[PDB]
Length: 150
Picture 1 (cartoon, rainbow, N blue to C red):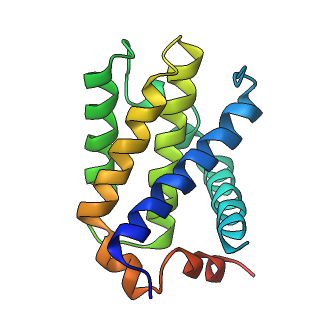
Picture 2: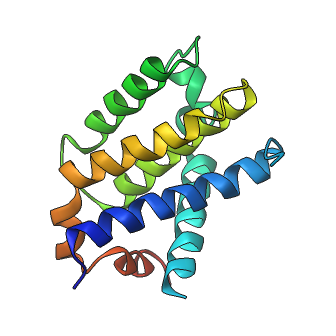
């Protein structure tokens, strides 16, 4: 029965881990239950990019991002996050939120804006806190994502 504070802290730690996996895999990272969740998240995110490459691969081009400035990335992330959930919350939609955040973060890092990753993580953290946290607690928390596969 996690608290809202813990759920948000885990949301940001899961974001950092997912992003770190993607940066390392993209080749631009030149620097228990939780690990289970991270592996599921990466798996479901990858499946999303596999099935819908035109939407989740090349996030920056999809959103028409030219400058990787802090206001552009933050407004791009928030505007997509708002549209993702307008019709309800599901685990698949949460996965899509992380996939958008990581696609943006990879593009920032490739364009000499690695400082932006901290901002993306904070934006996802605050969006979860204000939009999703009560739904997560009804599911039993992040561990419920293990029910998204077998």
